[PDB]
Image 1: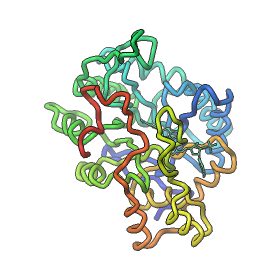
Image 2: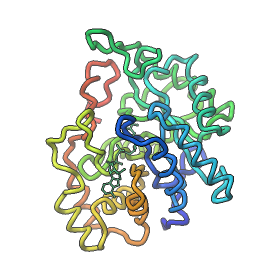
Image 3: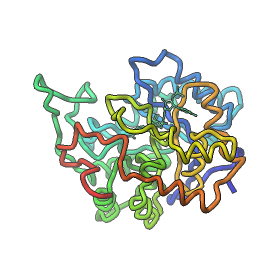
Length: 325
Ligand SMILES: NC(=O)c1ccc[n+]([C@@H]2O[C@H](COP(=O)([O-])OP(=O)(O)OC[C@H]3O[C@@H](n4cnc5c(N)ncnc54)[C@H](OP(=O)(O)O)[C@@H]3O)[C@@H](O)[C@H]2O)c1
């Protein structure tokens, strides 16, 4: 079935997506310049054909540098690489969608992106700051209009600037808003949300499957555990007893077990690593498989507790995690 050489799964719009990709979020403060570029190149050399990034990660130019270098040397052709970009909360105004995508295309120095998604369903005040706030720290929220923003996204696909359209951090309600939109042209093909053994997303996954929407698991390894977005009080995913015991069984690390778990269930995983050894380690998940019993025991680790709660925005009209799923 899935192999290092061939592991692309179908998207509802006729395109396909590599089941594993390299995540590229890294704290700008503690990340050396060029680390992303080096990592993307190593990832491609290793076998990765999917790179997940975002303009707001401040390293999209490094992602493009790496992809273009690998294409220039003949390591891969543009069609062999799948890049996902994202539209941040401060660029949801309809008239801003295309210009925002065009910026990313210029930053990457590519003609199109394979997948472009609404980064979060919440809309923030447009400007030169991703986190709009006043002297009181009070978050400057903007009226969201998902359907209108989606229509703008649709025009980008119509123009050929992006192959597939998707969303991120969208709950059932929000997905239905688009799925039931009058005159819907392009249905979302992917929903990128936190997903791993401690938060298996059973209900959202089933809902998405009913609409041929593929889930992409962000923070598939349980996050970098940065106190800014994660509670360091929670037990680390990679230290889980079962995950480590199963690792011993297959002589694989807990990270490899968790990644195999999700891809075996049809969930795309985009683990991030800027470390040579770990980039390679995370890709070695096609030489073994988990038994039905092991898959069930791993899914049973689900705590229905997420690592990324985005609690600072729980007051936004579009908060995604207030509802069950
Ligand atoms: N759309 C959204 O809202 C959203 C939110 C968060 C993330 N994402 C995307 O999802 C990608 C993945 O998530 P994430 O970066 O939060 O988390 P992650 O992939 O779950 O975990 C990354 C952390 O794990 C370490 N790591 C990587 N491989 C490892 C291995 N084999 N063993 C032990 N530790 C390992 C990394 O350090 P080293 O680099 O030193 O290996 C890093 O600290 C992002 O980079 C981004 O592209 C999207």
